[PDB]
Length: 240
Length: 241
Image 1: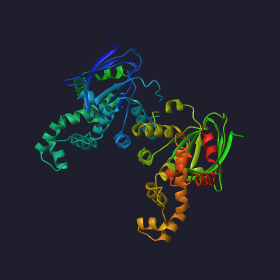
Image 2: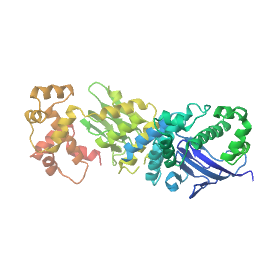
Image 3: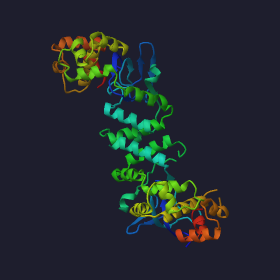
Image 4: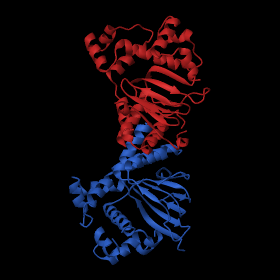
């Protein structure tokens, strides 16, 4: 009912640590599945587009508490953990209740220390550090993403990106297909992630379409309902 | 009485975090003084020769609990924290949850992480990170120490060190005097630190600690220890029981 939701194409654009205060979710890959339980912390690699089926316990509250890491913060944490330490199961990893998490979020300096501390206290840290390092790599898809990000309003083509990257169209094609993506999908993922964030933020549908680059908001509603499978209102009400 | 002791020339050869479980100590500089209170945590720089006057609460236990950092661990911690006057070399603080701190103390991938955590939680961390960086620098005196550390038994001269460092004797002299030390003093500090580390081991005895540190006669070593630290080796052993 109103406790359960099933949205697809969920892109972890930044490395996200995720509690499960008010939800039991099943995270789906193209071939794998990971069930996150309630009162547990989950580490999510950046660059992971996935489908989630959630089960809220209380209908009135948000399903979970999430914390994102900037690219900047992700590279400093990677460098710090490398100084210190020297498949879907590798990219999404849940753990036991910290039982002592005390929530920072405004002083990276204090935050990065606490994150290093939590990782050091956790077990099986090799895979956590591995996910950190992997998510700290600027793949070719990330560079095209950064390019498009500057003007989501602008209508891009493969030739524009190719000229910007000083390459041929087929080169960009095969690079993105080896990254398991494409230019159109990259663009859509960026726009729809910004749209979801803005929905849970204080733009609204009347202007989110324009902010992300779509002129007509009805087309944006249909495109959101296609990408995530949930109408923008259902997405808003499940996280409210 | 035996609750109080006053030993001089206490060299913090490794960056040491120091609790005060069973003591109230007064650290003395050539011109400054710092009184560490009971049930506190103390931060000390590497390369610090000081005097201490301690006051144990229970005569039967050790006065405090200390934790040292290897040069390797100190350099990692410095690099990690960079990624993330006597008052600027010795800094005490208050703690409530060292229960978390316990940790295993037998690893670098975990200890320095928990230490970073403690520092992040401690306010006024600026001077702490300062002390870390300063103690992570290999001064010329540290290079001479490392050279001598190889063969403490060997009898060194200023000319041997100078030839090893490809320099003149007066150069080594002025370098060490700018570091507020000298070759003979460097040697004495190294030997006497080891002596104290060889002490409180309850496994090694004077009859052989002098030989390990390079002194042939153990009576001369007793007199030299009682001169350097001001406490007879037996008093030093009994205060840290």
